[PDB]
Length: 50
Length: 49
Length: 49
Length: 49
Image (cartoon, chains in turn orange, yellow, brown, blue):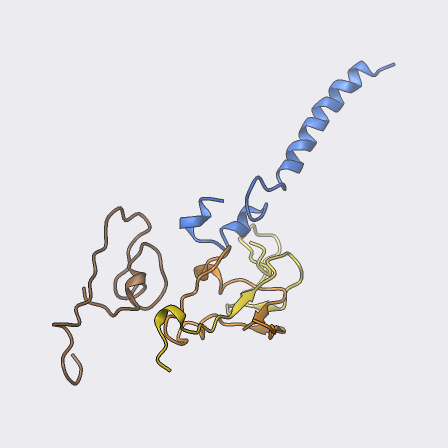
């Protein structure tokens, strides 16, 4: 929580299916979107952070 | 190695997206069809439904 | 029906997964109750049930 | 001179220009386009916004 490893993704066909078969308890909780319709849309720039 | 569940570590990754009408680059896996010129149809150009 | 532990959260009306999409899916109108409990005392045997 | 007959035209014109501006003004939702709210939400919650 002291350093944010922010890494934006570039132009690609991001398939939201690898996160399904992730580590145990792979809950896909969202706060404004829905995972059911979070794979059929395009994104300007997605920012990742661990 | 055997810490209590109340104080176990959690690896959490958030994916903040930009849900805007800007020209997007990170699209989802889908298919593509042909284009009609003078036929009223349902379009989904770059997310715009 | 009998499922695992981390898959009980998919019995709610509307969810993704493997059992909530191809094994047993509930509509988004279910006005009822879901009852589940740990059955590892009599439904878990040696070398796999 | 022809202001009393032009004000009724402007009143019937400024009243229609406010409906086309309130059409793209969110009244407590995530966006103003109805085709985008149903595109990134679930009907459990999509019917709320």
